[PDB]
Amino acid sequence: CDELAEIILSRFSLIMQSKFSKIFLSDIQDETINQFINKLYNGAPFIKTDKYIDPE
Amino acid sequence: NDYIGKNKDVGLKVELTEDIDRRIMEHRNRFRRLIFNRYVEFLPLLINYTNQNSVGIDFLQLEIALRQGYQVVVGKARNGVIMILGYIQSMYKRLTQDDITFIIPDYLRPDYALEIEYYDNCQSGDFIVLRNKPVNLNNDYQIIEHYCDELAEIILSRFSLIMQSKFSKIFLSDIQDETINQFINKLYNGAPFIKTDKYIDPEEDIIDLGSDFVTTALVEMKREYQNKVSELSNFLGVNSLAVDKESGVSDTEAKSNRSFTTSNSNIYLRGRNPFEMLNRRFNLDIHPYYDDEAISEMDIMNLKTDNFGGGKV
Amino acid sequence: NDYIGKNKDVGLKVELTEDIDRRIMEHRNRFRRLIFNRYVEFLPLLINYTNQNSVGIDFLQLEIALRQGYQVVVGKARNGVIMILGYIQSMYKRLTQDDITFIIPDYLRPDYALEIEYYDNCQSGDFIVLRNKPVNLNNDYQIIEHYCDELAEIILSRFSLIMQSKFSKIFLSDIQDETINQFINKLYNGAPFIKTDKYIDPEEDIIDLGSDFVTTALVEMKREYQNKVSELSNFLGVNSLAVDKESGVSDTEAKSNRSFTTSNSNIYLRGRNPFEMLNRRFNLDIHPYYDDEAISEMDIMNLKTDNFGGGKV
Amino acid sequence: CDELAEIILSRFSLIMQSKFSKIFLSDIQDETINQFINKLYNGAPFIKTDKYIDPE
Amino acid sequence: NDYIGKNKDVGLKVELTEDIDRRIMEHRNRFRRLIFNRYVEFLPLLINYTN
Amino acid sequence: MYINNGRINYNNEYGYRRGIYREPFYSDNADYNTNSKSYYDYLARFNGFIFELCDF
Amino acid sequence: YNNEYGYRRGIYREPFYSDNADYNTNSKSYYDYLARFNGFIFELCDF
Amino acid sequence: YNNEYGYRRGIYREPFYSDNADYNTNSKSYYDYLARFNGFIFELCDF
Amino acid sequence: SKHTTTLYEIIESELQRLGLNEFVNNDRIHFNDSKHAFMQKMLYFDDDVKQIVDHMFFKGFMFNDERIDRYFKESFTLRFLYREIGRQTVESFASQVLYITMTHEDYIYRV
Amino acid sequence: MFFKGFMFNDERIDRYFKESFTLRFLYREIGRQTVESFASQVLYITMTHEDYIYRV
């Protein structure tokens, strides 16, 4: 049970650690991001922006 | 000339991108509503009862009433025929027929009816009280609402990938270089050999624009869509465990838990347990079972041909 | 010499690109209309009934009327032969034949008919009332519209790939260099060995235009097209579960769910439940069943050869 | 149930996050994008532009 | 024309990101409650008796 | 768009009419499902007023 | 005129002579031009 | 006019003339502007 | 202007505050005057438009040289005539513009 | 219309520059919808590249 407890400690820590997110980098109050997220979350096959947002 | 709708003073319209975005959102909402409603219709039809010709119960109304949560009563009426009496209201001493809120015409109402009880080996009584589940801690419609949210989001992603995935061939040149129009005319029709000059540069001035997600995004999303539909069915009583056992699929092969979905189906089968009391009082054989199969023309032919069942994955 | 249609003063035509784009758009719209109308076309024929020779009932009109939403009345007329009496144009104590909105001729109108009810064990009555679905929360024709929109988008993408994917070989040289014409003539005909000089090197002056999407996009789009037509069929009653059980295709092998498509078919089979009331009243064996099979010459010969069915996946 | 609840947080956060869109980079009011998207979304086997907007 | 619910003076709403995060959190809590209650629901029915 | 007591004023009525069917968006009548047709049809709102103003 | 046999939609264009036209529209978009035109309609009524 | 025969939600806009407007909102955002407006409503009552 | 206002809208609003009218003018109505219209005025960078810009965007920041100031602010207001301000309000956008101007004042002077 | 009230000091420079501009784009469709937005962009480009145009 000592060997089983350690594995569960590692297995549970991996569950809580494994959480994914999408991170947008921009100026701290650039209201384009909020508009961009609103389009992206909903359906948006095509989004038009400028060169300065640099999606890649 | 060409046809367009009669002029209706509507004002200016938003561009095509906004139209497409609203169409995708409306498609997602419509799909969520459709699937929730369809599961609501499918729910009452899951459990079916054998030997329906024995008594005049009209089992479909019974199942519908049970699924909406009523405490339905079935028993013998003044005719002497077993039928759905009125539902019991409010309260969960033997019920002396004054507690039934009858729904039958007035002449078919027993003057003296007693609930069949497990004391006395169910050998005396008149009616039976049925409940949807033996112990109920969940609103079954909340489970459907829980997973339709997850199904709506996947469809929103799956439909957005369909509208996004459109390919085109793009020619780069001067804005009115009439060579391109000639070049496209040859290329679209049959043209094994086309002769041009060095300045058109086919390797880099002609660029193919693709979805970039057709290979992986479309395939992986349907896999996750079918997972969510699988989890919704297993959570409720919906199952295909009879066929799964014959085919030989496994828990690892088919991403589901047989033991979990088996017990969920038992929740409603054991809810119809009071039918054993009816089977014991009057000599009848009414046993609930899961309506696994919708009979088919091939199934009817297969039974006659004796070539029925089988198939190993 | 050549033939050309008589001069029609239509004006000036737009270029090939605009004509091709309009043709693709009309093709997409035409496909959407065709598939929606085809599904509406073969919707009534999904369910079929056995022992049609027992009663003069005209099952085809019955199914069409049920699908359109009517509440068809089936019962015995003055001739004494079971048929389709008129529908009921009212929302849903015994129906007394006054509520029936007759469509049969005058001489077939019963003077006194009573609905068969589950009281008295369906042993008395003259007619029954059928409805398309037991619980009716969703519009079937809307489900077809929801998926025909997703199928129409794929055909736009699939057809745009066929038109785009045209291959040709381009020769780069001087705009009137006659060495190209002699080169193409030799190359197109048989020419194992061609002799030129260094100023036209095939490594760079001869390039090829390719779709760049034939390897992947044509396969993936069709695979996604087959999913939506499969998702649409499973959502409705359309299924092939009788064959799938014999072959042994698993839940993950064919990207679909069995429990979902089984219960969907059960909505319409259980909708024809009142036909059980006819059997008890007049001794008859009429049971609905999904029409899973179209009779073939091979099948008729397979019956006599005794070799029917089999196989595995 | 505590370990199953953490997974659903991670599984559902992946469904909401995983939304695909195609971004066009150009000038903020360049009308060539609107004509491009309209052609691309509808059927358009062949599109003609110039070098100043390269799809690569 | 368009339909919108009757004006309710609720105040100012937080942005889409906060709403989505709260929705995900409530979804997780709801699933935990549902599965725990379902296991408690079908626990009594595991064992059955003959005759 | 009417002359009352010898004075002409243009009032913009906003009578609301709602149709049951959504616009098909796939019929051949809606060519390209673009914006321009709306702009073309907007200016027809002023035809009656223009004629009455010319007469006045 | 517009005589024809086939029913290909919206591919035939007709040339015409535009004797006069004023492109001086004092707005940044067609929407703002139409708004300015509504204002001008009101003030023309007043005038 | 707003006559419609096909219903699509929220894609049609109508121009209008904005005779007057004041964009000089001494606040860093709409939220703080509304807070300032509450304060100003109390001050205006007193005045 | 689908999200926030454009520079043209703010300048037009301030010009309307000043009391100017583009149509009726001096008892003769012109739809597109080409002299008093708000457009063809912010493009020629009239004195009123320069005062408005100096009041709102570059809050009281003026280069010593007159021609440098005029050309720099004309370029700024011409480049972003129809663009929408990034921030929620015009004060935050004005503060950002003023900061960027002050930080690069030496490069502007030399260039 | 396009270079709204903008003239270079020299007559020859101004004439040659503006005529080369109106020749290179004689048959090109106009960007940015309305004329005035395009005129503003052209004026911005000219005022920005004044020194280079003058010396070239």
Image: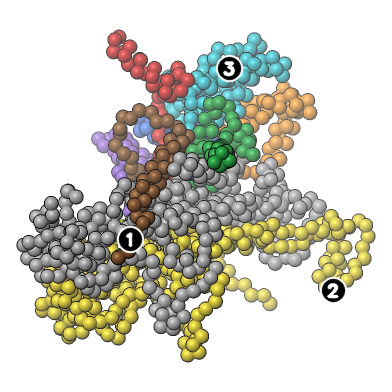
Chain colours: A green, C yellow, E brown, F purple, G blue, H red, I cyan, J orange
Depth check, mark 1 against mark 2: the one in front is 1
Q: Is residue C120 visible?
A: yes
Q: Which residue is mark 1?
A: E49
Residue F40: x and y in percent read 46, 47
Q: Separation of disc 3 and disc 2 at Cα?
A: 75 Å
The amino acid at mark 3 is: Leu
Q: Residue furthest bottom?
A: C304
Can you say whether I35 is above or below A21 in the image? Answer: above
Residue J53: x and y in percent read 74, 28
Write down the chain letter for disc 1. Answer: E
Relative horizontal placement of residue C104, taking residue C157 as reference (left or right): left
Residue drawn at x 18%, y 80% is C76
Number of numbered discs: 3
Residue C52: x and y in percent read 31, 83
Q: Which residue is mark 3?
A: I98
Front-most of A13 and J42?
A13
The amino acid at mark 2 is: Gly
The amino acid at mark 1 is: Tyr
Q: Which residue is mark 2?
A: C190
Relative horizontal placement of residue C66, taking residue I42 as reference (left or right): left
Label 3: element kind: helix
Residue drawn at x 74%, y 32% is J16
How dense is the environment of label 3, judged by Cα within 10 Å: few (below 14), some, or many (20 and up)?
some
Write down the chain letter for disc 3. Answer: I
How dense is the environment of label 1, judged by Cα within 10 Å: few (below 14), some, or many (20 and up)?
few
